[PDB]
Amino acid sequence: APDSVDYRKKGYVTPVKNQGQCGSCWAFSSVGALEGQLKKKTGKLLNLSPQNLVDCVSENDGCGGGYMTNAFQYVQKNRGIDSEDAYPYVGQEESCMYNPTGKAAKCRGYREIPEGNEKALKRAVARVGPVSVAIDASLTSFQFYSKGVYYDESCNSDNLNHAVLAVGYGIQKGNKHWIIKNSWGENWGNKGYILMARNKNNACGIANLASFPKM
Ligand SMILES: CCCc1cc(-c2cc(C(=O)N(C)C)cc(C(F)(F)F)c2)nc(C=N)n1
Image 1: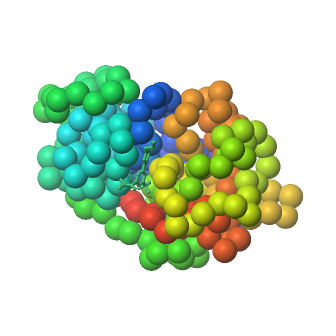
Image 2: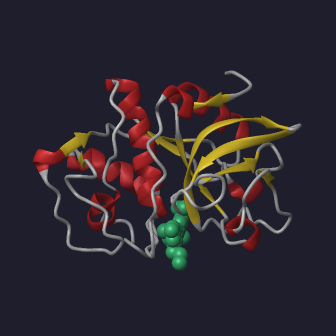
């Protein structure tokens, strides 16, 4: 495992999306992970459907939140997830309307990173690619992030309330970080991205609910 890795520079990461006024972070985290595996497997980079997940993952709560593991299971069981174009994002939950002709990827299971183990998350990112992670994104400091390696004393490892994508890791001006793709649009943070403190006692719970899909 290298000391720094950025899957964006390998072409594994799609443009930053905007979940709008719906608690579908978990769907965007899940599709980001699937996108990265799809590129690694097939050589194609393309947008998969978070709406497909929002409407059809019965184990999750749609715009009221959900888990990525339940998303990956849905895709496996369903034997497919649609492309964005085949099931576009509307930011509100509707009846499940999966379209077999628009299938753009499959899932053959998922694996979880041992809870709170940032070394294991690092190795997982280096060996697989982008990994779905859950964090405490509830602080005002998080909302108005612009630059630097995000750390706040008041972040809560036990309050996982937001889901994002770990697309890499490294170090900036002495400070180790995770490279995190968010889903609040390109005009949030640093072009839709945030660097979050790494190996600082599992800050914001970043390694407490990490998972990736198999393909
Ligand atoms: C008003 C915020 C609603 C909301 C909730 C969640 C959310 C809720 C839960 C959780 O506790 N359960 C039970 C699924 C868990 C998670 C995570 F990432 F840890 F798996 C996220 N995500 C978003 C993302 N936008 N929005």
